[PDB]
Amino acid sequence: AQYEDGKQYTTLEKPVAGAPQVLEFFSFFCPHCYQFEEVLHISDNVKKKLPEGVKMTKYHVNFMGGDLGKDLTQAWAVAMALGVEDKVTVPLFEGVQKTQTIRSASDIRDVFINAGIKGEEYDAAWNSFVVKSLVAQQEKAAADVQLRGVPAMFVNGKYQLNPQGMDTSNMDVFVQQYADTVKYLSEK
Image (tube, rainbow, N blue to C red; front, side, top):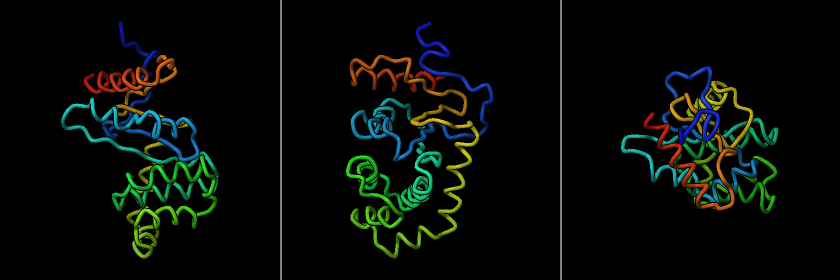
């Protein structure tokens, strides 16, 4: 076939019940994730090709960057709770990987302040049990698929995108192959 198991995707031998339709995992420490966000705009191109009626989920992971890695997962929980993902994603990526100006929880906080989230509002979110459970959800979703690498995308808790099986000579062509694969799996 044109799309074949173990080529553009792998099938999870252990399917996950009730998972988000389109589930993407990343880390602000993850170099391909930086590419995926700023150069390839994967999430956005996938969405442009997804059917009507599908929500898109994105979670941070703990297994990179040790102590700061966990702080970043809590901060992404804050970003999700406040609905400010689209204002902090780029400065967090660049703060971690480009300028290397993010080295503590306080520096993460600075990124949000600079993006216009109020101090009081951020610290209240940071310490809230709603963010606590949001952190829990992120961890549980990753644990359910035994996640050991990012970037990763899972469709309906059953299929896992396999970007190593797509050509990379051309970034544009890679992105559409990726997004079309998601569409196909969606319709599967």
